[PDB]
Structures are given as C-alpha cells and as structure tokens.
Image 1 (spheres, rainbow, N blue to C red):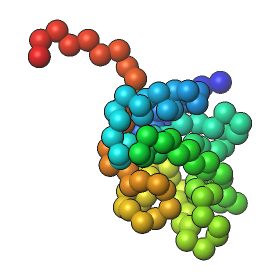
Image 2 (image 1 turned 90 degrees about the vertical axis):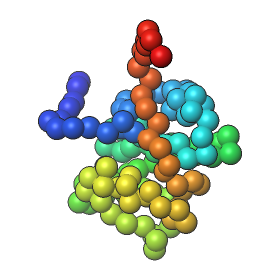
Image 3 (image 1 turned 180 degrees about the vertical axis):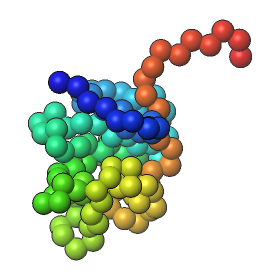
Image 4 (image 1 turned 120 degrees about the vertical axis):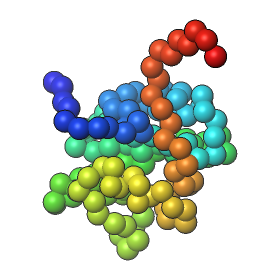
Length: 119
C-alpha cells in the first residue's frame, strides 16, 4: 500500500497525514500565508489543502472529476477551474481574491528531524 513518482518533488505536498498534523505544522510557522496538502483519509482519490490565516486552519477537500482532475470543491460551480496535476492546481491558487482564505505565501516545509551543529 505505497506510492511514488520519478522526478523532483515540492515540499507543500506532505502526503498521508492525520488532521492534528496538518494544523500542527502550520502552527509552527505561524505566518499569515502558510499552506500545505495531504491525502484525504476518507477517500484517497481526493486531497486536502490546509491554509492558515489569522490563527485559523481552513481545510479544503479536493474531489476528482470525470477526467480524474483535481478541483477544489469550494465555490459553487461558476468560479472553479480544472487541473489534471496537483502542483498545477496549487500554483494557480497562488494569487489572492480567488476562493481560499489567504493566498499561498510560502509552502510550509515538512516535519523532518533537523539537527544543526554550527549556526
């Protein structure tokens, strides 16, 4: 029950993680422009985009389309685009005044053990 792809990969695409985690990470940064993605527990075919703002985590469910395309089911059905790739969907939502609470400022890094000796 694993997966993967060949080629460089972003940092905002954490992966299969629990809710507590989604927020946990954001908290660390504490910036009014943090964001991240994860695999929806309920349905794998779908994703979950978390956006921090004014100390509030706004999760966004991404259900697949007839053409296996990832499209945020936020808006009703007028101001919504359709992308086949995940990254291609995120970037697009980099601008403000779209649908999310805040515009993706910096792709919050994963939670890996970092041990730096010298400054």
